[PDB]
Length: 216
Length: 215
Image (cartoon, rainbow over all chains, first blue to last red):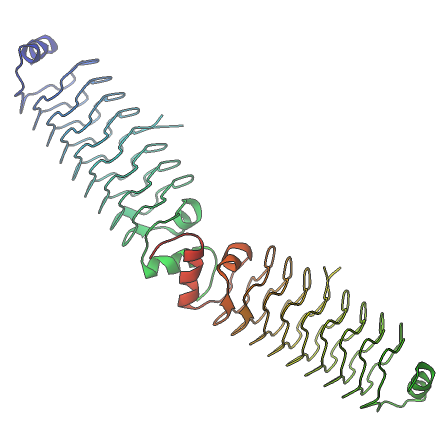
């Protein structure tokens, strides 16, 4: 299916486009709210500035898709493939992104995506850039953040239980009131992140002290 | 006994002056090394710049004594009363000061040197040790209530079982100190350098907590 066809259909009030192939498509500025694009192929698709608010994108292939500046508020992205996707400035506030693959995804730079209150449970964000991103209130229970860039990323009140932050850059990260229990973190995180009211284990508290040079 | 008598005796090679009353005495600059002054009364004595190296001053009353700039290296001061004593610039390097009462004592505020001193069980409550050097000192079980340790150097010091409640610790260097079991305020965790400092599990927790972490 091409651009014109699908815009027409949406304008007619059609909302079921599930399984549709839209690889490489130019839907810049396109307005597709409430659209069911579950299981859709959008590999390398240009959705720059698109409005996808409340879309069903569950299981969609969005690898290396440009969503830069797109609206995805309360979109269902569970298990969506977003590997290498360009999301700088995207609004994912409230989105269901659980189990989604966001590896290598660019979510901001010295600009930042908004993921406030998003569900990122079990999401694979390994190697992702979230520098300056906003994840205030987000659920990252069990999320993989290996080698992720969280420089200046705001994670206040976020749930990082059981999360892996190995290799994550955390300079300027704000984890105040976050729940870190059971997360795997490098000792540098203790040195870099602000952690006021952050919730931790006993093992974590010890690690925190040790990371400041204390011996036991 | 007055000044002249005792200087003469020392110059003769007499060393036993134990129990001698020298209250209020002016022994500024006096040189009294190896002197046994155990149980001596030196209340409010001026010993400014005195050399007391290797003296036995055990149980001596040195309350409000001016020892400012005095040498006390390897002196035995165990159980000496030093309450309110003026010790700015004194060298107590290597001294046995255990059980000594140093409450209210001024040790720098230019500091005194207490390197490698034995301060076990010493009462230093309310003392001023600002800028003092206690590197390597043993303060096991010492009372440091409300002590000023601003910029005091306590590296490799033993603070096991010590009470530092109310102690000011801005700029304090506790690197490689042993803190196990010491009682400290949470502010100490915030203010002192603690690299290689040895701590309890309960201390590690308190440390985190003092940085705002919740359990």
